[PDB]
Image: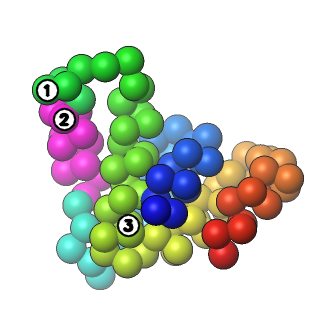
Amino acid sequence: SNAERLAAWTRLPWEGLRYSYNRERRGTAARSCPQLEADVALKAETQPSEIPLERQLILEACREAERFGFLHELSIAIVEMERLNKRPEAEVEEIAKLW
């Protein structure tokens, strides 16, 4: 889905991306950031791999946004942060095609 697309495109660290997820989850029953972090961390150690935990966290967060209906708001929020990090507009265009 667009959750996997957004998670693949973003280059933000979890330390920053968590802010957008936490901001856009207001009013929903989506998991908080510590709940996501604990769930993914356990899921990572029950099936250990070379997949960075940060990538699993971000993908879990994008999926959770899709489940509770704020993936579009999260994509806009993530793109705002990336543009603040001067992510090139040519690359923002690649994710803007979901809109």
Position of 11 relative to 93 (above/below): above
Provide the residue designation for mark 3. 65
The residue that appears at 64% across and 69% down in the rendered structure is 98
- Give the amino acid at mark 1: Thr
Q: Alpha-carbon neighbours of circle 1 within 10 Å: few (<14), some, or many (≥20)?
A: few
The answer to whether marks 2 and 1 mark residues whose Cβ atoms lie closer than 8 Å is: yes
Secondary element at image label 2: helix
The residue that appears at 27% across and 77% down in the rendered structure is 28
Along the viewing direction, whichever of 42 and 8 lies nearer the viewer: 8
Relative image position of residue 30 (x, y in whole percent): 25, 67
Secondary element at image label 1: helix
The residue that appears at 23% across and 61% down in the rendered structure is 31
Q: Alpha-carbon distance for marks 2 and 3?
A: 19 Å
The answer to whether marks 3 and 1 mark residues whose Cβ atoms lie closer than 8 Å is: no
Hey, which quadrant is residue 66 in on the image? bottom left
- Give the amino acid at mark 3: Ala
Provide the residue designation for mark 1. 46
Q: Quadrant of the C terminus?
A: bottom right
Q: Is residue 38 magenta?
A: yes
Q: Alpha-carbon distance for marks 2 and 1?
A: 5 Å
Q: Magenta segment range?
A: 32-43
Residue 19 can be seen in this image: no
Between discs 3 and 1, the one toward the N terminus: 1
What is the chief secondary structure element of the magenta stretch? Answer: helix
The answer to whether marks 2 and 3 mark residues whose Cβ atoms lie closer than 8 Å is: no
Q: Alpha-carbon distance for marks 3 and 1?
A: 24 Å
Provide the residue designation for mark 2. 43
Q: Alpha-carbon neighbours of circle 3 within 10 Å: few (<14), some, or many (≥20)?
A: many
Along the viewing direction, whichever of 79 and 69 lies nearer the viewer: 69
